[PDB]
Image (cartoon, rainbow, N blue to C red; front, side):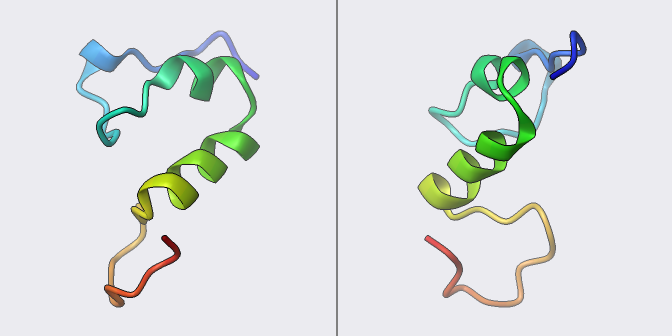
Amino acid sequence: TSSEEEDPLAGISLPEGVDPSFLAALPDDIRREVLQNQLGIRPPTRTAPSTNS
């Protein structure tokens, strides 16, 4: 991990419910895990509505 934590008031692009404290304080592994699996949202370009969700 790093001390460089992303703050929610810093206008960072996260879905609702997803707070960056556990994302920045814990590794990037479970960070992408919780984003992709829970919300189904993809930061890369959406070309398929039937995504991993």
